[PDB]
Each structure stands twice: as C-alpha cells, then as structure tokens.
Image (cartoon, coloured by chain):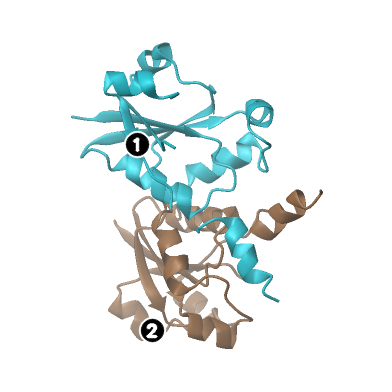
Chain colours: A brown, B cyan
Amino acid sequence: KNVVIYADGVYDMLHLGHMKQLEQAKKLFENTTLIVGVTSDNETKLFKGQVVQTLEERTETLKHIRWVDEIISPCPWVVTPEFLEKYKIDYVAHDDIDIYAWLKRAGKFKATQRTGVSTTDLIVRILKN
Amino acid sequence: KNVVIYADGVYDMLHLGHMKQLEQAKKLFENTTLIVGVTSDNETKLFKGQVVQTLEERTETLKHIRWVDEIISPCPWVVTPEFLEKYKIDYVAHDDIDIYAWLKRAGKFKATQRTGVSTTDLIVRILKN
C-alpha cells in the first residue's frame, strides 16, 4: 500500500508555505514515501528569476522537514515519464496555477496548495520600526 | 531505553541554526522523545528583547521539524524540578554560553551548539542589490 509521491521545487528560503505544502503531499494517502526534488542553481537561475540559497543550503533545510522522506538533489527541471519509472513514482505533487496535462491524463497528478507566511512577509513586520 | 529530552526556546524565525540544534538534542541518545518548549509572547517580550512571530506561528513552524516529537506551547520561562517530574523529562537540552548549574549537578543537562544561517544573514545576501 506504500505510495511514492514526488514534489519538486526550487525551495528557496523555505517558509511555512512550503512546509504546509509538503505536509499535504505527504498525507495524500495513508502510506506514502514523499520524495522531494530540488532544482539545481544553474537551472533555477537560468529558467527562474534567481536563487537566494545554493542547492546545498536549500537541500539541507529540507532534510529537517518531517514530511520529507527522500531528497533528489539536484532534480531535473522537467519531470519525464522515464524519471517516473526510474524512481517508481506513483504521483507528482505540485501546485497548479498546461505543463501537468500529461500527468493529469495519467492520473498521476495530485494538486497541492499555497497559503502570507513568507520570510518577505516577516521583514515587513520587522521594519515597522 | 526511551529517553525524554526537553529543549526550550523562543524559536522566533526558525532557521537552520535551530534545526541543527534540535537534530542534536534528538540524537543525544539512541532512543529519544524530544520535547520542545516554546516561550509565551508575553514572557519573551518582557524578559527577552521582543518577538517577531506569535506563539502560534513559532509553534506551528516547529510542528514541521522532523526532530520534534512533542511541543509544550507555551512553556514556562524557567525549567523547575517539578516541571521535570510532571513531564518525566530525563535531560534538558540547551546551548550553554549559571542558570543550568543545578541541572548539571543532577546530570540532566545536555549541551547543544549553535552554528551564519539566520534569516538576517539571508537578507544581507539579497540586499547586495
């Protein structure tokens, strides 16, 4: 009954938003292995705006999160069919704002939601000085 | 063989520093229950400089840390003998920079160390703009 779930992301400056999202992935089913994939710095910088924390900083932080069973660091930018087989992943867990069409067609896409909980927020609170 | 360990702190703006410190507490012995205690906002504000995150924000964040088995929120400011009995705590795990004398006399003080990993640090990295 153990189901493998895979959640990839930049995971820069992990805040409660990410943690809630990982808890959710982890609890999609009764028995799970949550695998998390962490984008390389190169790919993030070149496809995403930037990256504050290095791969090793973002990965070490995820190590400490209760919902994380396994880390793939760095992970590929785009999940592929072959990547699913290689790692016996049953579902991909990610938010949905269509890159995930083929996953939804397969029944292997579980959506996860964001939640005002970011470091950026916290500073606003501080600089009320 | 299950040993109860207790680590209290403000735990404002949990960063890798705190997480490493909790991992350490958790792995003092082979079988542990790490209990973490989180100071009230009132007491922190009145004894410590301030507090950025409310009790509930600091506690919810600790919920997500793998090394945390149990939370006492809010915890008392000063650990007492009676508090140890009440909760069957075997050791208090805290850094040591003597408020902990009587604990060391009892053999119930396990020291834990800090590690350049704080949110404050991260912003410095960002505002290199």
- Given residues A74 and B93, the one toward you in this image is B93
At which x and y percent is residue B87? 38, 19
At which x and y percent is residue A35? 38, 65
Subunit of label 2: A
At which x and y percent is residue A116? 70, 54
Sort mark 2 into few (<14), some (14-19) or many (20+) by Cα contacts within 10 Å. few
Residue at horizontal 44 percent and vertical 60 percent from the top: A62
In the rendered image, which quarter contains the N terminus of chain B?
A: top left
Side of A1 where B44 appears, left or right: right
Residue at horizontal 61 percent and vertical 79 percent from the top: A50
Picture layout, residue B38 above or below residue A18? above
Q: Which residue is mark 2?
A: A81
Residue at horizontal 50 percent and vertical 21 percent from the top: B78
Picture layout, residue A2 above or below residue B11? below
Q: Amino acid at mark 2?
A: Pro
Q: Which residue is mark 1?
A: B111
- Given residues B7 and A1, the one toward you in this image is B7
Picture layout, residue B2 above or below residue A25? above
Q: Nearer the viewer, mark 2 or mark 1?
A: 1
Q: Would you identify the image quadrant in which residue B56 lies? A: top right
> For the view shown, which residue lies furthest in the top direction?
B82
Q: Amino acid at mark 1?
A: Ala
Picture layout, residue A83 above or below residue B88? below
